[PDB]
Length: 164
Ligand SMILES: CNC(=O)c1n[nH]c2ccc(I)cc12
Image: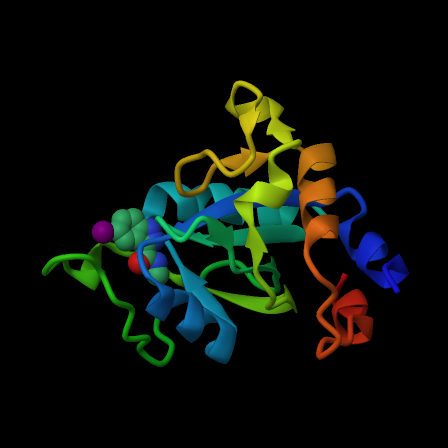
């Protein structure tokens, strides 16, 4: 069913995450973590205090798809176990901020062809697939986008609901 999912998304905030490569999304799915640039880290930390749920919707650049979505379970923190993120070219991971803990809500993919009817008011009503890393997605568009994903029957949202 979709009822617990709708409860988790009620009055949520949504952010588009653009990963440079599939390796980083695979690490995030395995370890329940994400890290971003300080400009976006500050936005996500503000949002985490401001909303019942903050949802990250992931898309690997040039893949033509979203790879799933997850809910922040913490503000960013430093000093944890290192994560061997992959960065394009020889760019240094030192530019990243802290680490957010996340709980995956859906690990299934969704092709951009299926979200063509959704526009994001916070990005000039462009199709929701279009946006820089960290672009906020307005509530209604973000909710409908998450509801388009195939159900992920491996996930039990009972534990997530307890964290709200
Ligand atoms: C695991 N997160 C990243 O690798 C990442 N997040 N935002 C970015 C902006 C520029 C570059 I180069 C890399 C990133």
